[PDB]
Image (cartoon, rainbow over all chains, first blue to last red):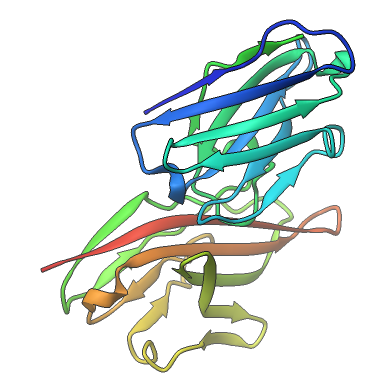
Length: 121
Length: 118
């Protein structure tokens, strides 16, 4: 299994980035998929998640409305649409896969596979 | 934490017995208040078993007499199906609800894929 993120880099305030996570090695349509972030020093925080079997979306209150998670099951990829980038969002963002269904999507411990992360500023 | 330990997949023998393990390490001051097992039907999980304050409840007659859930060891809520049918093949979800020390409820679930081999 690999999860590979992309789409980060450098941007100033109020801008819009788009993150993507290509998942390789399972049929991840039956996995819940999630986005987390870790700003230097700051401990890793939950951003957004999307459940298996079509299913629902879930977001942190800090990024809610600004950010949007989506998934393409044919491409085995998950996305994160990030509008209105406040500078505190400067972190590495990681995608992750787990076998939760409708609960526990915020819990880092619930995820079995992690990407390398894409740096966002 | 807490998280459930459930295999990615389980293969059972046709017309035999299968165990779908679901365990967790009991947490200090966490009270188990609900156990559910669900079977996936498209985008909808469908409850097939409930353990609550009045005991165990099998919600479909197809399972009565052949679905049982472990209960002797705290933290082990594994599901056993007897006389495995071809069409028992599915994704199954184990779901546990606890009362927490801070007074809230926390829920965890985890999915396994059940395969039936001829």
